[PDB]
Amino acid sequence: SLKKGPFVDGHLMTKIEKLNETDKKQVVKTWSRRSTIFPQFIGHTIAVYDGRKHVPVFISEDMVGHKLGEFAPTRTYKGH
Amino acid sequence: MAQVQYYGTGRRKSSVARVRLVPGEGRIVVNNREISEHIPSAALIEDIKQPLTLTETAGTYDVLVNVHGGGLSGQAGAIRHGIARALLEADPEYRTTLKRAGLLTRDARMKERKKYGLKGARRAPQFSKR
Amino acid sequence: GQKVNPVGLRIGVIRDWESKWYAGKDYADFLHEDLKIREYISKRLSDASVSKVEIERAANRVNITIHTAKPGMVIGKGGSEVEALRKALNSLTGKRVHINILEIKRADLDAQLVADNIARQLENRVSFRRAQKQQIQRTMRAGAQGVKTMVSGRLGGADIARSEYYSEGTVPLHTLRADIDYATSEADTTYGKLGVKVWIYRGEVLPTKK
Amino acid sequence: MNYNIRGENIEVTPALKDHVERKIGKLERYFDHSVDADVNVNLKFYNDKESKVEVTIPMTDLALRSEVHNEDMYNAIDLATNKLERQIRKHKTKVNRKFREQES
Amino acid sequence: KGPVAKRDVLPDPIYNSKLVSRLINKMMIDGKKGKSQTILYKSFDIIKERTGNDAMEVFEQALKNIMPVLEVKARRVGGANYQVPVEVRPERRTTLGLRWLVNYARLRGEKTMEERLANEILDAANNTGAAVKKREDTHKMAEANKAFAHYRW
Amino acid sequence: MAKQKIRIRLKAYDHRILDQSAEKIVETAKRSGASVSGPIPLPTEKSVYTILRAVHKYKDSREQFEMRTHKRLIDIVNPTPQTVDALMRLDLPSGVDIEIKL
Amino acid sequence: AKKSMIAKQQRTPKFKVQEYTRCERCGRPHSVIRKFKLCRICFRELAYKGQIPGVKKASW
RNA sequence: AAGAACCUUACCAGGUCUUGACAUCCUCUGACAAUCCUAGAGAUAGGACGUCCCCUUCGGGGGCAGAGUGACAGGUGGUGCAUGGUUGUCGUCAGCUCGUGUCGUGAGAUGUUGGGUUAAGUCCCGCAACGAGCGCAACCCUUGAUCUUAGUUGCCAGCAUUCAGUUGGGCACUCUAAGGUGACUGCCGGUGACAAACCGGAGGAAGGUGGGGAUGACGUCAAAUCAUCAUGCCCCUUAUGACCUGGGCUACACACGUGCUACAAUGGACAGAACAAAGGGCAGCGAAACCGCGAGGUUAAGCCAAUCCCACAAAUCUGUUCUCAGUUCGGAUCGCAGUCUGCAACUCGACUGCGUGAAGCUGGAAUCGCUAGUAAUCGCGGAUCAGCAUGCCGCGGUGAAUACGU
């Protein structure tokens, strides 16, 4: 993105407006990988597509703009 | 309308010049730029001035050379080749010794096209030694 | 390792461009159109043996000047089948193409009809020496500077390498101003696809001018 | 750099890797010192019971290799090494020639 | 194939030099002949202005003390050969002198390879040094084996 | 100055259709008035584009088909409106591009 | 997968940057010519048999 | 591979469907389908909105779609030791064969060997052989010389014209592609068994196949390809098939392979000036103007293109300066900050800013390519292609040394 702007997931934007709207929902799968974490979508758990199964990622406060699919591990390590 | 002088257009490596040498005093600056204005200096200007220094060595009449094409040896070598052939059109008997002091043939040494799988038309592909 | 398109090697230097057309802001509809009409006569020639199919682009109307060995075999019963498959091609590509006809005699001078017809004439249980010598006698005796026909590959089942290129007479295979007709076909028998490739170098035309 | 071995259609067994590796240890058991020797081997008895081997050793400034067929597939390795015998003795003798003489 | 000879060059910029025209033909590296013409003309003004003397006499005495005579042509029956004595031909003379004076003098290490190369040719003007030391070097290796490999060729 | 001269420029696949077809295209310019200009020869541009001439391997052994397409031009001088509208009777060639550019 | 591969490559793309080029006579990927409208093998064989003007080759 | 963020994609995980994504055929209804909404990350599943023929005189004809319904469809599965087709090298090296005849019980040979000469089994001459085939060559294209045709957007001498061949004008020159001409040992001096060829010279733009390209002999390697395509058999089929999201093909103790950029003063940074050729451009190129250091943004004249754009060439020349050092060299790594492309640049596009400044001071044994516009070197354009070049294919610029000899 360059200027307009940070590209939200859409489906993750609906789940973030809903679960971040109220009640502070618990972590489930979220098969998207496109955008980052959001301002209001913090706190939750993204069990995003690690390729085989999910991986519980924290909705932290340090990775403000960092990619929500970047927190997961892509290729199975390590290693030799 | 001027004196009957050289106008001989010849090429050398994709740079054909049009030397127009009138009855003059030795002024060789073609296309509005002098020999020290077009491409200085550089002691190869003596090589681009030798063919006028060979047709009895020399007149010297004027020099007006419209040279467009090639590079340093293209514009310069085409200028000396054009004033050499058209300079053969200056004096009608100048081809006796001027034809034997080089001063012709427009060598045409341009780039060779590389084949399908060559480096630069001379660079070989590679060697896997061992 | 060499082998070369004789029919593409001599094409454009002495041979004729078999596909004529203007070109063009849209070369794609021309290229696929000419391929599709080439398979149009290709499908419609199961027994006619059209030895060439030239199509000309003529401002929203194709001129598919289909050649044929025997005239009435594709020419219809006095205009029936030619108008039928012709108009059907008009609603097959989208352009009302007034397809003409052609009568190719001298089958030893026709490359693909004589060679491919020799191949399908081999697909009926005919032997390799009988098929190759028979085509060399009919088309090889029909009149030409030299015809050399070979059926290369599977024939006889096992140890598949079989190359009987039996053919005699002169051949301008490397003579670049020869203009030989040389195209192959592919026959598919029960043992395997064991096709044939033969060319008939009929004779060159001397270059002149005025 | 020495003694990489790979093979299609088969395992990369260490009882095949040391089996080829000891037997290819005869040449550098015998020569001076090299760093070389990639090996290829595969096949079976799908048709006409074969096992192609082809072992290359381009170390002594000009290449040398061989190739043989068998079904037994261990007994073609020996028939690769003793193929390399003459190629590695005739690399050294042929070149180790003392027929030199001036005016005698 | 036979002896297929080569062509020479024309007279130089300053002034009418021909062997020094070959000196400019060796003077460049990587094609750009303008930089070689500049460094060569800088050696001409540096050695003809500084160290007050002429030019064609200075180069004629440098390469005149640089153009060798004998040289080493290898051979043998095989292992442990004999480096034979093989004297130079003329164009091999000027070529070998251009190789020794160029490849020795341009690798000196002064403030510039142009002025420092002129200092290497000026030290070569004393009949010794880098280039003259090489002419004595090959001139000394040959004639060390000039009693055995002389009448073989 | 002059008038905007009516002349159709030719484009062809080979070079003989523009030559001979430009000849009979001058045969349309003999009638219809006068002043049909001669063969202003176009630049004759080509295209050279090669593909990998093997099935899978042999990446060095390529092949380079290249097919050029350029034809001459003709621009008439005298107007002749009856022949100018009569230029639509174009019969040849099979492969040729006529376009009245005026 | 020639039928689903080439047939799916004939269908409508997902995004606008999804439509990738396909093979002309044989639906191969990998360098179908966009100006001649054919593949590499298709341009070679169909061009040598006669497809448009013209040959091909060997200037330059 | 002439282009991997998804598609590509075959491979993995997950969710799906089983005459199926694509086709023919029987019946059968329908003109089909689209457009939004929801749930889903998606394929999909539900709705609502919606559709509801061109030709007969009813029986139609006709695709389209749906269903049954099995005949079928599929495989980028296995077999390149079943194959066709195609392609490498041996190699542009000059060979490779046959008809007839003769020899020899035979296989075979002879021709094709001998004498010269060539790049050549090229040519000539002897010869128990005489002939022909593919090869060699030439014919084809390009390249340096011109003639003739023909001058527009290209060229501008000869006139007026300006910032601008730009514009009245002009078709001399250059240039443009058609026909030709020109080089073929042609000619002379010889050498040579007269013949073959070979040494030397004039003349010419060009001399002994001008330079280069295309062109690759039978055969070899069971060489490469069932994955460009087609195809014999075997095997799978409510899954080795089909659809979708994400990932991977880009991983990383390590060894190689081919290239780029460097290690530096013939250099590094700047300022000014000068020289090309080639190709592409309508689903496109993008002028000028302003904005942004910047990459680029905005709008917009023009160009379907010898006119306009890409476009400015760069190495090179003239001055300042760095001065021998891991540096005012070189450039990775990596951080922050922006642009453009796209459904989306975190695995995984490039470019720009500020910063950072690895290792390298010409590289071992060994190994490579190279006969002149060549090596080497400096830039430009293009196929793929939304983006993505240090590769690939062409284009021009600077301009070398050596070949003693086998």
Image (spheres, rainbow, N blue to C red):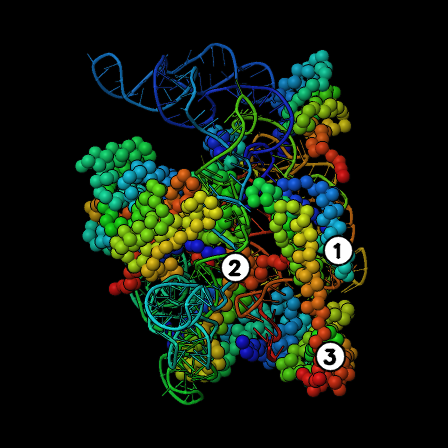
On whether disc 2 and disc 1 are found on a single subunit, the reply is no
Considering the numbered disc 1 on the image, is that residue within a helix, a strand or a loop? loop
Rendered location of residue H58, percent (x, y):
24, 12
Depth order, front residue of H334/H140: H140
Q: Quadrant of the C terminus of chain E?
A: bottom right
Residue highlighted by disc 3: E82
Considering the numbered disc 2 on the image, is that residue within a helix, a strand or a loop? loop
- Label 2 is placed on what type of residue? Lys
Q: Residue at x 64, y 25 (%)?
A: A32
Q: Nearer the viewer, mark 3 or mark 2?
A: 3
Residues at circles 3 and 2 in contact by the CB criterion of under 8 Å: no
Depth order, front residue of C68/D104: D104
On whether disc 3 and disc 2 are found on a single subunit, the reply is no
Task: Indicate left or right for H236 with H257 as reference.
Answer: left
Q: Residue at x 71, y 65 (%)?
A: D92
- Label 3 is placed on what type of residue? Tyr
Cα–Cα gap, marks 1 and 3:
37 Å
Above or below, comparing residue D16 to residue F71 in the picture: above
Cα–Cα gap, marks 3 and 2:
44 Å
Above or below, comparing residue E97 to residue H326 in the picture: below
